[PDB]
Length: 307
Length: 307
Image 1 (cartoon, chains in turn orange, green):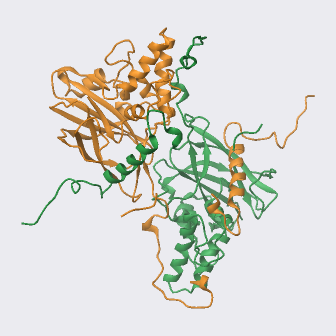
Image 2 (cartoon, chains in turn green, orange):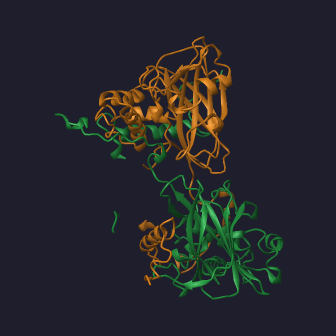
Image 3 (cartoon, helix red, strand yellow):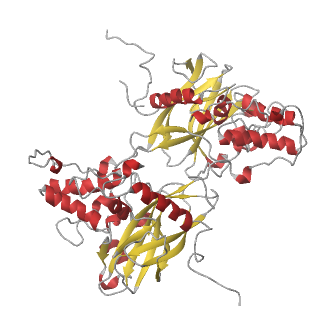
């Protein structure tokens, strides 16, 4: 049992942010996608004839069981075709838990809705890097060995806003055992003194992407834990340093001077010869009126009457 | 002579934002990419032995000539191989103006540096749309006819932060004449009473992209105007409506109520059972310390001495 703590797993972020134990309809959940995931399960149970308590129990079970996003592969857990067709064929971020009446594994399908999932934001020191190493931290709430991990990254065409995650959109970037190590003092895992940690080079993506982590027990029960983690690289601003021409080293003089371990925690774009705030407000209105299917075409300049 | 006013051309945005006439080194320019473009030309002239005035003149000429981002194709302006190999072979956003000593067309190569160019931000009403119509507005400061336009969009793999725009990264999405029309009262073009306007379906992109516009005169001189425009689609937030399960229509009762033409111009994510502001501040530090080439690996947990 466990979950990804770095980059924080999707369901783990929803669990820790809280606000889901009460009110029962999930209206106290602040993140819109955690709230939507909760409400999809809550509304699914209500549509199928369940009471408010059955619906709140089903949706709260999805959040509470953030360390049991699991599926049983049985003894043939090394057969990739068995995993992809029988164990986790779909609803990958729910670990194929699709039955609210049967526990384990209940219904965790709210976690597979598409939309604006909140990502871990990783700043780039230089925008031309091809890979960024991240030190993964997986938090085991229950220690199980022997085991191994697989880590996947979504293909570049994946769009978190509209797509479900599927095996055909995942690229394996890590496969093998990770030994248990003592958690560091800054660890994100408070449930245990041991964590699984490893560095993987993450292919840089220009869009928000998903990392998929599989923690598979090497045993005849073949229990595996599957978690989605939402991530985005944040680009450094300014000119690409490789295109930057520097001035020659110089010393100048004249009567007009204008001629020559801790860190820090729109009207700035106004100049003496341009009111950017005013222009940009008019430009924002222009975008709204001259883009999209409901744009101003002829009505502001054409008048008609019925003969 | 002219420039794209909607979506605003790159060089046109730099011109209108100002701050470049003085001080001469461009330090008064507020947008970092307009400032970098200016300073690249200014520093190029200084490196080649020019004075401060020659360097400021060259860089200011690049901004002032926002309606003359042009190249002469001669009588064979319809030959695409002549345009792509001889007229505008490279420095596409400068219209291949690469000679600060020779005017026209001077040196406008600062406009082809890569980096965080400020885009026109177009909001999406629905994230699943495949194309978004935009009504292009091209502002002619001098009226010339006959003429035609070509509009291109960068390929999906284009990365504004690191790449120069090239013909191999451009897809034609419009070719033909656009008739002159009276400007609307909300027009972005104050230089003339006539504009060129047309609607083009823009392929949705999940990243910041470039629109390339060619305004070609149909005449033996074969003058053509070439402009880059930076654009980004802004996604709508929340659950993808096609995945949204709605509750059945219901009426409930009980003693605990918790059981059941103008528009508007982080502590919100705290709940009663989670301090998000505190957690996220610790999570931001974790990202900085456990990602990148300078991450904490062994130094916080390992000590060594020389035998």
